[PDB]
Length: 129
Image (cartoon, rainbow, N blue to C red; front, side):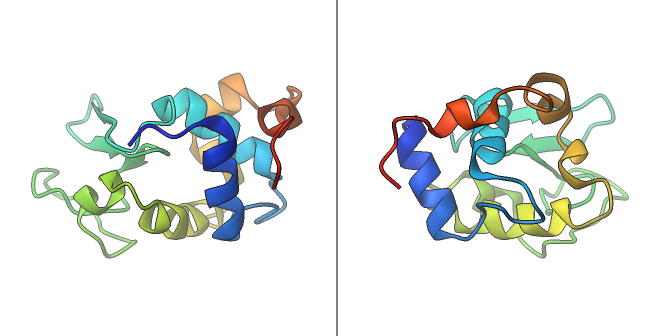
């Protein structure tokens, strides 16, 4: 599913991602925009042979099982395919763990390079939330 911007905002807020670990909703929406273009089915291979999945491009190196990342972990205890669903619950729950790992949203390189230090509230402006 490809979310609309305000649609994703509302879904993230309902799942309690807004202000989670101190990251306002616009941070999360901006991360999703640049990781996936709001597309839950997004997948991308990394150099190391791991793959990133879903709206927040969660990496199989650490966080989910895809059956093909030898030596990786599965710290969210889920198949990576769960992160591609139209329902973002699994992505949100796993993102909550990731953002709690010590580096905050710097875990998402696209957030660091495209969202951090910008007017992230722009990503939720206009939305009725």
